Length: 211
Length: 218
Image (spheres, rainbow over the protein chains, first blue to last red):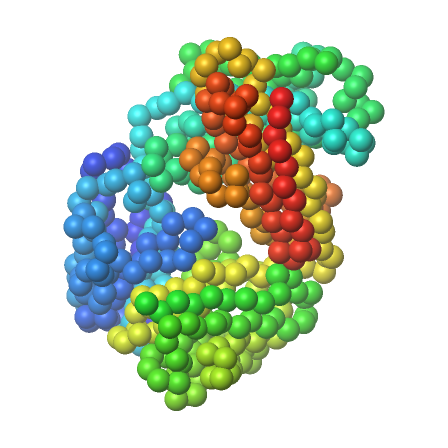
């Protein structure tokens, strides 16, 4: 089994800039090497036929080069759509193998999160459980802090967070924090608050509701 | 113009046998290119399992072997995959492809997920999230459906039957303490639109065969 090794395993680049990825191989694979682009929740896409032959649909920005032990994929100008993970695989010999994969994150100018808060549904109160969610809409970078306050009391161990993949268009992340409480405990309180701390924000922003 | 699609069970108990089938359309397997099975565990790299030639020839990857068998049914234009003594590691998305020539795959399947758990299936509940109370602001507001307590993944959410696709964020599910997946899908719309425009989340769940639609109103 031939083993391919890509570098870097993770990469963060500014838009409209050159991006390079290297793929070193255990044995010389000569001409036979291919490149794939895999966006999240999608099947890999053929970027480059063996050596550097373009694919019929791949932009001019996408390229490649190499022979023997070493191969290099180059993105001449990084675009918003390029946000994905890239794999290299070899076709020299069976069994076929793929690279470790290279994730490329677009480094866009910092933007502040648009925060919203949602009260639990009346239909959910009947269930006996109450879930409160705080929304952090579009924001870069991905790093963010969420604090839950119930009647100005800091809560811990009852919140779960989910983060989405980088957007194809605006290259911005999105985060959702879910606070789960029993109906019994949900109604023994008045004020619920979500505290968001981000680079875009001068001071921590809190969005709250009552009743 | 070749297309491939994979279908099978969403969930399989451990120590059982995984069975999958890929359906080829626009080209008969009996002639031409050889056809492959590729899997990718969540947040990990792709793994090549094996292939079946048009000729009916079959070869496999040495690792994972003795568990894998590939077969085809030319009459239905299909080629199937079987994995035995399945464990938690085998949890992955599975791909259909075409070796083509020179061992590069130009055409890939949509990909189907299979998860290995002894747990049973549910059964999602769909709860609406209420949009902002400030309708006078004229700015952008946000609403969404909450999909909770289902197993296993995945679930599919769309808005207004696919009419509304812009500014929609569907968060990846997280495993709750209850042992049930849950997620929220939200979309930002102009606050002025709330009165005139109606918003509906189209939620669909294949394993439990559940299809729920929910209107979102203040």
